[PDB]
Amino acid sequence: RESGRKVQSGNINAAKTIADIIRTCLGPKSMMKMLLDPMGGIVMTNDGNAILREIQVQHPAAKSMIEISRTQDEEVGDGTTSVIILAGEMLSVAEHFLEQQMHPTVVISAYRKALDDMISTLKKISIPVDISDSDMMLNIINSSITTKAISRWSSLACNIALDAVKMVQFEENGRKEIDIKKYARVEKIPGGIIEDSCVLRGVMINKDVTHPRMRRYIKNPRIVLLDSSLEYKKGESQTDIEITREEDFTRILQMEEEYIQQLCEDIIQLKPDVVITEKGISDLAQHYLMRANITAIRRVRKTDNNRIARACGARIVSRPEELREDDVGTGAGLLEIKKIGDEYFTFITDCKDPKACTILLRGASKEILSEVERNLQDAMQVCRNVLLDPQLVPGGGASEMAVAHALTEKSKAMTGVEQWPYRAVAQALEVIPRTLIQNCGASTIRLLTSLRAKHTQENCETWGVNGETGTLVDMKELGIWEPLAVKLQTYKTAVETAVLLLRIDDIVS
Amino acid sequence: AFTELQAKVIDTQQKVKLADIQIEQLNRTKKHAHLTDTEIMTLVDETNMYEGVGRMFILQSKEAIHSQLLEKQKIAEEKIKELEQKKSYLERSVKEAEDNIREMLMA
Amino acid sequence: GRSQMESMLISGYALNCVVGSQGMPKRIVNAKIACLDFSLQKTKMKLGVQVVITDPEKLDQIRQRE
Amino acid sequence: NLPQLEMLKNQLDQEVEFLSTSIAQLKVVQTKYVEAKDCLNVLNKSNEGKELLVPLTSSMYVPGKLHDVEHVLIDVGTGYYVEKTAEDAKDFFKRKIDFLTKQMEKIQPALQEKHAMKQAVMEMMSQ
């Protein structure tokens, strides 16, 4: 039970401090807040998503801030800090005034037009990419890794991100939307080195299949994904009574044989060696296949088989009758039990569809690998974000100072009370520049007013202050870049986010 | 894995045994079932022949008493096949699971 | 898809369906319909129609005759 | 100490003996219901009026003329008898077998389980 202006305050109130301390933590140049547990447990992070947690949370809109944050933590995970900045910016500025000017409403609307102007300006301020040139992509990843200051192994993982994620990218609604991630498969591996890893075709099966009787290598036998229903039928097509006695053992187990084979001969109809048996797994099912000298890999996940559905690019087959390569094991394909470290790894490569690879990771060991993987995970996603979005923007204040002018130019032209949000919208761009001016550790009011001028003539197209260069700069020469969507994705959120709590005057239990 | 491949060699080796003497018993039961026919067949017609199974012996005519009793022969002759069929199948099974024990050991 | 202006009321029901991919007739006039909420699929019959094996073909025909 | 492991071995030996006996006997008792079931098919067949030689007493067998093939007994209740139709009698024979069947049945699950646990004690024995 909470009300109105006090909500509206608690909106501005909480969302203020919500938007805040992690901006000290923001920037490649940053300030890590300390976090103390009531027991005395200490934490040092630049991660708001992490910072969101140990702090005791009460304000349910702060919980809701954690929501769009986690919601964004789901999407990128980076900028979850940066998304809640601007809503904090947004909710702070227009709300109290314009609610004391009596409305969420004109505030609500104008962020539609706060959104589009930049969305427009985004397509203007962001420039297309070569996803064709991975180096044109690499610098982004070279840029993506280094705000949290990780380079060492990532410098390679940068490239390896480029490689698979363009391949792990095959997806179409017919408008060809590519979100596809789960295709990309990663491998914890002991030994090798962080500077040695790769992407192997199909989907390499690492996690739950070490299984040594897969044989080892499949030259061109098929791998078989069973939504069969390979389960032995104790009768003709059915499962007869159990075996409590000698008579039920002879007759029933015999008919259990046929249904395995007749399907496994349908499996043989696509000629495998490896059959990874998921539905209809039977102790006779593998044994027959093992009697068939068909290695039947059981006690297995359909997630593996979904990895294997993306390992051969295939589907999994409920059809008992007439099992096919294109049914399961699409394409010639491979299957190989590989030891990277000594861990057995099934590698099912050569998906029937091209753009087939999945990321092998070697560190000097699992951990220093996990160093790669975690950062590669960021590296690899920026790809499918650049692969998502083949436009990208000179960052910092360039990203920031661009639209406010058009926005103010709107507010000036729009000259409503919607102009007031476009004023409230204008400088909210510049807070991370303030943080960037924090990042350099300089005088913001100057650099703002300075960068304000930098948009008066240059129009801050490439010109922000970059706290890490310290100065108002071209962000193209300087090379500050993100795929446009990510900018918007950070930008889209806070609008709706602010607009979200812009709706709430009422908490009620 | 091996356990289920161990489980079939045990379930076979126990149940493969009985059918082997089971055919033997019926080969015997075929005999008197046939021979109990001859003894009353020895009397060329006897209507004070009593065909009866248990305690009661009801009066009947030896004829159908024999018609029963070559079948009783046959019936007691019959399952020996089944009881040999049950026999021969299991020895083939014990080595199969014994194999996937060993080959999956080797793989 | 197509134009945003080509949205049309259409005669009866344009299916959301899997069209017949076997070379299905793409027009059957005046359709007597079987609307199936029931999947046709298949099941394994250890012995289908006939018996005789005159061919290794005929070995596979029995369970195929279903 | 030393006798306790010696104790439970041949202990579980006998449960095998007991249950194998009980299923054997519950293999026995079922067999006479179909006997009561089948002897009625014969008496229907030949006819009421055929000479029946039934036991009289020890070594004694007594004759009689068959009558009332439709009048045939089911022994049930504590001390009670229901003579039943030629159809009905054969039914509860079948019934009380099946009553005995799972009665007979679960004995071997009980039978076979007691030996390996003797073995398990015999395993620890030579251990």
Image (tube, coloured by chain):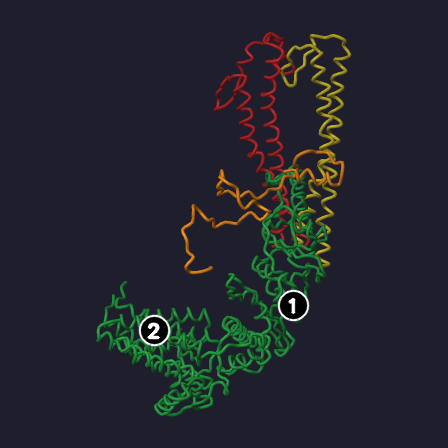
- Callout 2 secondary element: helix
Q: Nearer the viewer, residue D19 or A5?
A: A5
- Can residue D8 be seen at all in this image of the molecule? no
- Give residue A291's mark: none
Q: CA distance from mark 1 to mark 2?
A: 55 Å
Relative to A507, residue A464 above or below: below
Name the amino acid type tagged 1: Glu
- Asked which quadrant contains residue A111, the reply is bottom left
Q: Residue beneath label 2, please?
A: A113
10 Å crowding of disc 2: few (<14), some (14-19), many (20+)? some
Residue A343 is labelled as 1
The residue depicted at 62 percent of the width and 77 percent of the height is: A364
In depth, the one of A173 and A188 nearer the eye is A173
Which structural element holds mark 1? loop
Between tags 1 and 2, which lies in front? 2
- Image quadrant occupied by the C terminus of chain A: bottom left
Chain name for mark 1 = A
Q: Earlier in the sequence, mark 1 or mark 2?
A: 2
In the rendering, what colour is chain A? green
In this view, D74 is above or below A77: above
Give the drawing colour for chain C. orange
In the rendered image of the structure, the colour used to display chain D is: red
